[PDB]
Each structure stands twice: as C-alpha cells, then as structure tokens.
Image: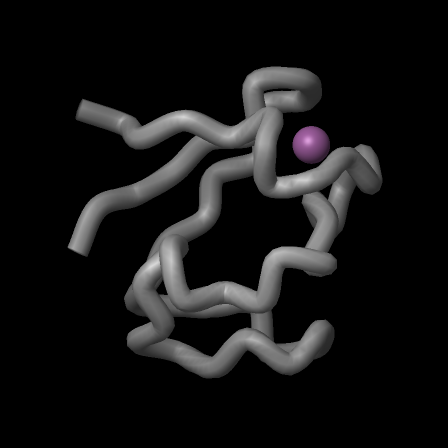
Length: 53
Ligand SMILES: [Co+2]
C-alpha cells in the first residue's frame, strides 16, 4: 500500500501505522479511510492529500 502526504502541512499517512487515535486502524488503505477524516496535524480534508510515488 502507498503512503500519502498532506500537501498543506507535510504530514505523511503511512498505511502500516494508520491513525488509530482517530479510528483509522493499521493496515487501512488511504482510499478506505472515512471521507470525513482530516489531517491530524493541520486539520485539512483528504482532498488535499496526494500519493507519494
Ligand atoms: Co496537514
């Protein structure tokens, strides 16, 4: 699975780690994260993220 970065603040979503404090368990692909989730650091929505390639 691919890493995704927040293009506003630089937070990296790592699917191996998830974001468990906000209910995103380890092993969750970015596409499967609920669409109301926001960047844990800067608070922007998923639409400001992009695949790290
Ligand atoms: Co951010």
